[PDB]
Image (tube, rainbow over all chains, first blue to last red):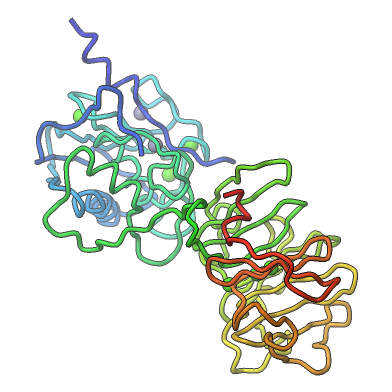
Length: 19
Length: 368
Ligand SMILES: [Ca+2]
Ligand SMILES: [Ca+2]
Ligand SMILES: [Ca+2]
Ligand SMILES: [Ca+2]
Ligand SMILES: [Ca+2]
Ligand SMILES: [Cl-]
Ligand SMILES: [Zn+2]
Ligand SMILES: [Zn+2]
């Protein structure tokens, strides 16, 4: 199945700077 | 550093990228240049290579997007979210998207495309966020300064835990965040700000609140983008809410995050001679209105209340403050005690009895 594929999409990471 | 759960990493050293579309904020060549430079930060310290494709599907697909831009992780307009990236993997994995609602530059203004990209690509290669504030992979952006970019030690250690070293690091000495518990630690400058201690070391300062034992670590640029990374000396004017900061022959007056009108000034305006190249340390006393300015083995006393240097300076540190050696790295005072930092030691000095009363390690100011 595709438990293994979604794995990258959880760990999506953002980079932030406050307003 | 931190890596991704299950330690996601690429199984191949030869990686391809493609710039799918471009920001209008910069020219194609300038953008190609930033990304190339961003991949080199990582390739310089690893066995990895990066090849740019002009069509088709690459491992790292790069795109600029605004708000909802395809994946269901929309951007947020100006500031805030700058970009995002997926860990190693097929399809989305290794991909990076940049918020075009930011003004992307190759300068200090807007948001620096290379700087964000290097960070993003760290994710694309398997680094998670770092807790080290001096680390490229720190979750919060800071423009690092105008000098050439060196990848910090933490990120190098991180990336190399996945892929090993390269053959030739062009810049083998990588900047390490200072360790407050190292007994050899020596300090650049010390002051108070709103009750709390400010301890400067290289391009960092710790802020330490007296109700706390653990100091918060900041990049100096995160407070004051227009100030130097490293600084010589610092003092305060408690009432007035003012911090003064020295570096070479320039000084700033600071009210929180704001540089007062007419700074930086030249330290000559303070009445120092021309052969003074830097103020090594400085401290102000609220009750008398007088500041002490140290340089080499001498002291000046400036009268802040009448804006002139007191008579009979410079004097010798050896003569007015016997027993603390020949220089003063940093200096602050409280409750009638002056704390003189000289390499890895600090001398607690009693204004009251005019003598040293306690000797303790420098890093002891950080509850170490
Ligand atoms: Ca991909
Ligand atoms: Ca944004
Ligand atoms: Ca834009
Ligand atoms: Ca100093
Ligand atoms: Ca000081
Ligand atoms: Cl100082
Ligand atoms: Zn990030
Ligand atoms: Zn996206």
